[PDB]
Amino acid sequence: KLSAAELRQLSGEELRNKVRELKEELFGLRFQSATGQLENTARLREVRKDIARVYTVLQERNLNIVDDP
RNA sequence: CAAAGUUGUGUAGUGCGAUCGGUGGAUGCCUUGGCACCAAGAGCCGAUGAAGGACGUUGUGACCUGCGAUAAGCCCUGGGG
Ligand SMILES: [Mg+2]
């Protein structure tokens, strides 16, 4: 569970690196789910919620909802 | 013993009554649903793309509800526990 408060302290480039890392983790989780692995099925949804959190932070910086560092 | 005579008939089935069941879903009692109104609102939405949908969306098979690849959900804010 990422926190939007922490992500709001990160800068844009590290936030996008976080987006890409989360996408890669979701890819790996889906492959494990397909192949019979993945005991931890909650992380499969939590990584997508984390992607949503990072997108919310990035877009609120883009739309000036919160000041962009 | 023989004669003459009389009377009787359920081993197939059936009727009526009682009794015991089956089927059926009436009756009674209800209700996550309607009907008729009352009081207060609100009286438009849409190219910043509507009304209405198609497809997808859950850990997993479908459907309803919600949502849209940020997909039964993301953030801020107040409440509450
Ligand atoms: Mg019945």
Image (cartoon, grey):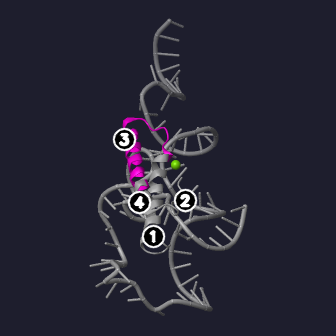
Which residue is denoted by mark 4 in the rendering?
A: A13
Which of the two residues, B27 or B31, is positioned nearer the viewer here?
B31
Q: Residue at position x 40%, y 39% from top?
A: A32
Q: Position of residue B15 (x, y in %)?
A: 49, 43
Relative height, residue B44 to residue B68 (above, below) = below
Please report whichever mark, 2 or 1, sits nearer to the chain's N-terminal start.
2
Q: Chain of mark 1?
A: A
| Residue B70 location, quadrant | bottom left
Residues under labels 2 and 1: Cα distance?
14 Å
Q: Chain of mark 3?
A: A
Looking at the image, is mark 1 or mark 3 nearer the viewer? 1
Which residue is denoted by mark 1 in the rendering?
A: A61
Asked whether disc 2 touches disc 3, contact meaning CB atoms under 8 Å apart, the reply is no
Residues under labels 2 and 3: Cα distance?
29 Å
Looking at the image, is mark 1 or mark 4 nearer the viewer? 4
Q: Residue at position x 49%, y 73% from top?
A: A67
Residues under labels 2 and 4: Cα distance?
15 Å
Q: Are marks 2 and 4 on the same chain?
A: yes
The reply to whether the residue tagged 1 has its Cβ within 8 angstroms of ligand 1 is no
Residues under labels 1 and 4: Cα distance?
13 Å
Q: Which amino acid type is marked by label 3?
A: Phe
Q: Is residue A17 magenta?
A: no
Please report whichever mark, 1 or 4, sits nearer to the chain's N-terminal start.
4
Relative height, residue B21 to residue B9 (above, below) = below
Left or right: residue A19 compared with residue B28: left
Which residue is denoted by mark 3 in the rendering?
A: A31
Relative height, residue B67 to residue A19 (above, below) = below
Looking at the image, is mark 3 or mark 4 nearer the viewer? 4
Q: Position of residue B54 (x, y in %)?
A: 29, 62
Res A6 label: 2
Q: Which residues are magenta?
A: A18-42
Please report whichever mark, 1 or 3, sits nearer to the chain's N-terminal start.
3
